[PDB]
Length: 63
Image 1: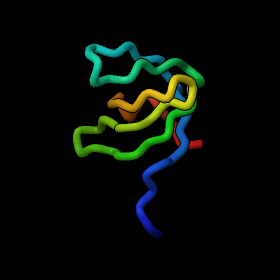
Image 2: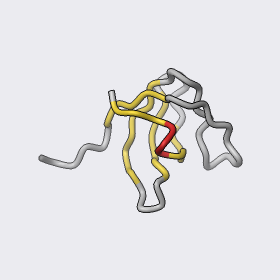
Image 3: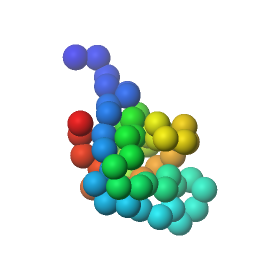
């Protein structure tokens, strides 16, 4: 019941970052979601490169 801050997701649609605040997503990447924002952007950390940043939530799916 305690907050989930490391929720495992898979990237469904690749996303190129518009700035350094954003994460590059590649299809198939594993991303751990720390926060889902009211504006629909997620904060998470990629397993592949260890980077933390913001990305559009609709581009990922729960595992």
